[PDB]
Every structure is written in structure tokens, then in C-alpha cells.
Length: 35
Image (cartoon, rainbow, N blue to C red; front, top):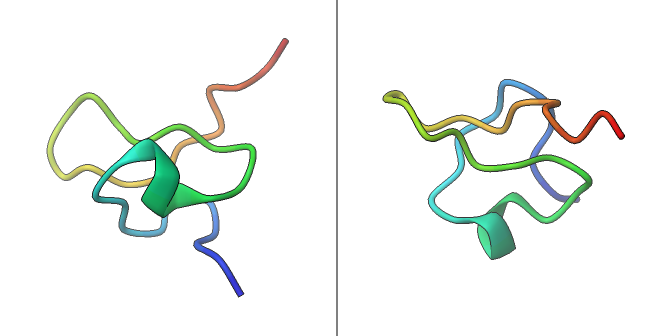
């Protein structure tokens, strides 16, 4: 299982899902993928 939204990320490839690693601290996976 990979990280969820508002889950802790260290990098994009560590965030796994269709979530980006935050560009703000604390770096948590955010659903800013909305295309």
C-alpha cells in the first residue's frame, strides 16, 4: 500500500499514487493533480 492524501511524502516517487509531494513543509501528499 502506498501513501494516501495528506500522507507523509519524501519525494514524488515516494508518494506513489496520483498525488504530488508537497512543495511546502510539512511535505505531505496533496491532491493537486486535478487535471
